[PDB]
Image (cartoon, rainbow, N blue to C red):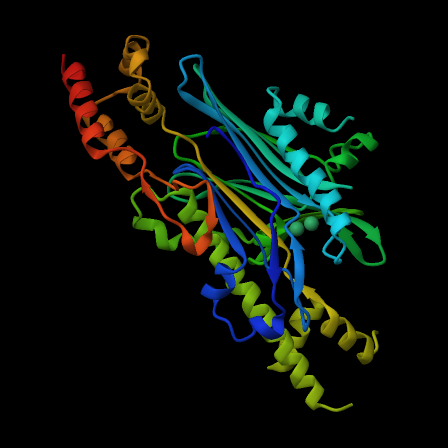
Length: 417
Ligand SMILES: [Mg+2]
Ligand SMILES: [Mg+2]
């Protein structure tokens, strides 16, 4: 469809003691789902959350992600609204608490998509009559200007904008506020209407976007497992994101991938994030068993966990009773090509062939550029089921090759005239 939003998901979360013998493949397969809109927008959603020695029977995913694809008056795709939310609190083993937190997480996301206003007006309408952080954006083609993207981040979500060669252009950074007693927690969408200092909480950027730009939104469950970087710290505020050099290396794979799906991009980041998460939790329980041998290298390992006077007994209780991981969600969007979307509309809506025919002349500089457009459309893949387990993904061609070839021949003939 044009509108897709993740549904309430309750999974069985095995303990670290059970996951400590499992490979990455098994860990991902039991914990993550693919929610697909098209080749150019996909969601991966799941939970890496685990107790050291106890299984979590009802592990409710408190993250939501959603998209509404928008069209011009002719029905040609020209924009989208995208939101990712992280419900604050929960994961304690109370279903009533998790249900309440999920309702706010989901409605926050849903309300953002259903609003038809610019981002600043949208945030005002959905923040007036349980907390959730939100990272969200609106892009739209403005005939004179091209694509303009409005970006909003409240809390510890993260948005990264790349070009078509996976060069990092912009980052809408995560935020933590100091709460006292050495603890930093993200602001919520709901906190925005309770204070005059909306800047201190709301990160806003308005950006010109190019065709084929990649926008990645992640909850801290995904990007927090990658190598992180402190961007800035004031008195009571921290600006945090991914190490840009490390994040760039994640795409080394796709360097020669002709037109990679949003799914493939999301999968690669999710795999690396959960690899580090799985190895992190392997190390912890083995270190715990290693420092139980003491009976009161490893030093740099023990140092790395704690620092990124407390009595030994308290630390061990902490490490042995600790939950690891979190609700982990990522959405990936490709900014559409003007020519590709006009061709999509021409094929899907052959009734509107007269109205669309005049628009091709402006969007076709050469036959080479037409061939480029039909090449991208040739490579588009869709998940016939909107949702399925990440390891049970089945993808088929968006178009019949024979349909694309006949349309290209017709359009090529008319260009050559
Ligand atoms: Mg949360
Ligand atoms: Mg989170």
